[PDB]
Length: 168
Length: 166
Length: 155
Image (cartoon, rainbow over all chains, first blue to last red; front, side, top):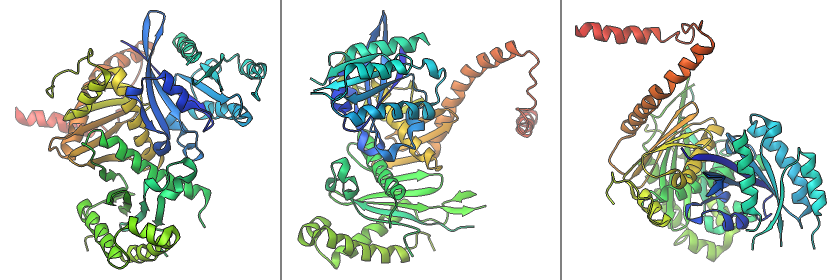
C-alpha cells in the first residue's frame, strides 16, 4: 500500500505560505478554504528512495479565530513545517509560539523526535541565516531551508521531512 | 424542559468583505437568543466562524450538487436553515431544538421547508416597505442606514417569530 | 463514464476529478485525523483533499459539542456517521432517505469491524492470555439474550 503522510504547514498569516505551496503542490487537487473553515487542503506526490509517498498538506490560515480548532487540524499529524519571512521579524519570533502550540494541541507520540522543518521565504533581510539556524539547532536540530516563491529548496525540504517521518 | 427557540440568525453578503481585514463586513445583521431582549472578541470570532462554516459547506457541496448551495443542516441540537434571498445575500438561521431531561427533539419544530418560507416572507415584507432589493438599498441609502433599517425590522420579527408548529 | 465504472488512472487529473464529482453515490471512510481509509470511487491522490475538508467540517460541530448528522444541497444528500475515531460519510444524488443512508454506513462499519477486531483481539489475548471480557461486555447481555431467543423461537 502507498504511504500517506499528514503534513501541517504552520506560520503567521501573510508570510507567503499560499503562494509558495502553489509552486509545489498539485493545483488540480487543491481545496481552498483558508478564509472559511481555516485551511487549504493540498496534496503532492513525493519520492523517498524507491517508495512513492502521497502527502496530505494542511495549510492552516493562522488566524486567531481558528486557534481552538487546532486540536482537530493537527490531530494525527505525521510532521510539521514552520514558515517565516526573512524580512518579517515578527514572523520569525512567532516560530517558537507556533511550535509550542502545535506540540500542545497535537500532543504527538515521540514529541522530542517529531519531524519538523523550518522554511525561510526570500524576495535587504532582517533575520540572518545564522540566527535562524541557532533557533533550529536550539530545538533539537530542525532542518533549515531558504527558498523563494519564484520552488528551489521546497522540494528538498519535503523529501527531508518525509524521510524523517518514515524513520519513526 | 426547554422549548425549541431561535438560536441565532445572520444576514451576510460575502462580496462585502473579500479580505481578512474586512471579513466581518460581510455581516449586516446578527442576532442571538441572548441579543433578543457590546460584542466581545470571542463573540466576534464565533460569528465569523458560524458564517465562514456556512460558506465552506456551500463551497464544498457545490462540487457535488451542480452548483446548488446547502439549504438545510441537521445537527444533534439544532436545525439549521440557509437561504440565498437574492443574488449574493444570505440568511443563516439556527433553531435550537427542544431540550428535555438532556435529550433533543424536533417533533414540535417546523420542517426546514417551512422555516425557509417564513424567512423569505419576512424578506419580502422588509423590501415591500423599504426598497427594491438589498443591493439597491445598499447603494441608495448606504451601509449604516441599511444595517440600522435591517436591525429594526429583524429584531422585531425574530422576537415574535414562532419556530414551533403551534 | 458509467456509475459503477472505475475512474481511469491514465486520464488527466481534471477529468478524473470531474468523473469523481459526477458520481451519483459516494461512500467515504476517514479517520478522525482526516486520513482517508476507503472510498468507493477514486484513489488516494485524488480524494485526500476532500477528506480533509470533510474532517474539518465535522470538527467544527464536534468543537461546538453539537455533532453533525447531515445536510442537503439541491438534489444531493450528505449523511455523517461517527463511530469513535472513524468518520463515515455518504453522499447521494439518488432519492434515498437519511435513515437509509445511515443504515448503509452502519453496514459498512460492520464490514470494517469484522476485519479489524479479530486480529487486534488475538493480539491482546497473546500479550494477556488471562483477559476477562465479562467487564467490557456488561450491559450487552440483554441484547445477547434477545438475539438468542429470536433463534429459539424460529425452531
